[PDB]
Length: 246
Length: 228
Ligand SMILES: *C(=O)[C@](NC(=O)[C@H](C(=O)O)c1ccc(O)cc1)(OC)[C@@H]1N=C(C(=O)O)C(=C)CO1
Ligand SMILES: *C(=O)[C@](NC(=O)[C@H](C(=O)O)c1ccc(O)cc1)(OC)[C@@H]1N=C(C(=O)O)C(=C)CO1
Image (cartoon, rainbow over all chains, first blue to last red; front, side, top):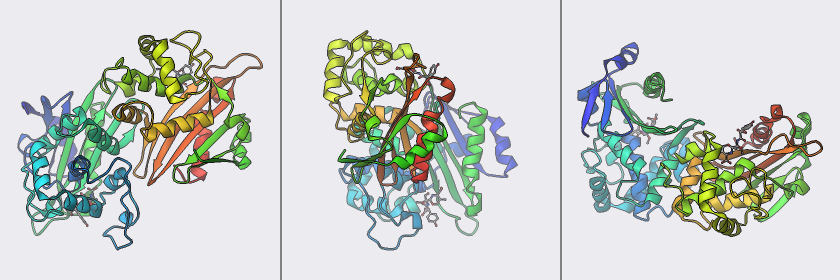
């Protein structure tokens, strides 16, 4: 990505909560990014829900998802989470990480096309093995904070191998905070509580569009208890708040 | 839209603030609308700042505007009036006039200065015409590229929530004259779950202190309706 510099100051936010994780921030572009840990910044973790971003783009590119206004009909059958038991729009499905909607999209896309696009997007290790509808939920797919940032930058610039149209559609679906001075696009992820001495990973990736400047970020941390999720946003938020970004 | 129904009960929020104005709320699924006053819903007023929406679309379509990053959202949000007066100048009266006709925007009267006709000129548009215009935008049905309509749609985002996204733009023609108060606007649409709500609000105004009401009143109505 060119270069990545360490920023020891941000570490306090991690120690305070006794959290092991990383934060990567890049101003203007991925040419110059700062982080609190050079090693972890490029370490690859299961993307979990953050994979819904590329999954949505591929869905539109392949025609599997007709257009930005397609409704994902609930068939009445029981779903893992109550917030998924109802019809959903693309933005709706992304915001609540509606697994079954994205699993149906993945199956329709198929393994050959999914592989092809992850290669075009240089998405992490590009490993989709272990089942077309769950590789990003419990498979071998892995991606780093640095790679996430590069991927989001391409999206922001409409440089991914997809129509500008489809890229714009997904970007609007990722808006999570709007303010007169800045628009925030982001996506959270959580692999789970993990196994015996093998914690899961929690994510928060996205970018902030200001008046004349854009900031790209990616955050991930280890986690063994779901009651820790709040940290996934507070730490990065507290940091970006410190930089005057948000 | 498909139909409109008058509901005088909303006048509640209007009397409370002692304000003369109208609110138009349309449900996309049922294609039906509701308003506290049918007559004023069709009354056409100066679009003011709300004109930036069609303005921005025309600017991109005519190439006068680089791209969403040129940023456009900054141009529509972080004031800078001269910025859009620039775009209008470059667009020209011939093209500008052509797009408003394609858009079926108000009375399509752009006389009195190609760079201020929407601020003090003869251009007039009703609340109903605003929601119809915004619906065409939402459906990418305006005579412009989908890409440009999408760019403008995101630039107009003013509130994001897990369950909904609000797109909107305010308007203000000034305190006006004596028995001729100015007009304040708040138009936009809300994407709430799988439903879409288009809205248009305007009120007579002679004091900038009451300016906050253009958002305040419509917001209370959409809350009581469980929109936002
Ligand atoms: C996305 O990250 C999320 N969870 C998972 O993808 C994850 C998995 O299967 O890998 C999971 C699934 C079910 C569980 O009971 C626990 C973990 O949903 C697709 C979602 N994202 C969250 C987040 O904000 O990070 C959540 C708190 C809940 O899961
Ligand atoms: C419209 O947005 C604009 N500005 C205002 O109306 C602004 C406001 O209400 O927020 C305001 C209010 C009271 C004041 O005394 C001064 C300003 O007015 C038309 C203006 N118009 C633009 C345009 O392109 O039409 C702009 C780019 C900037 O804002």
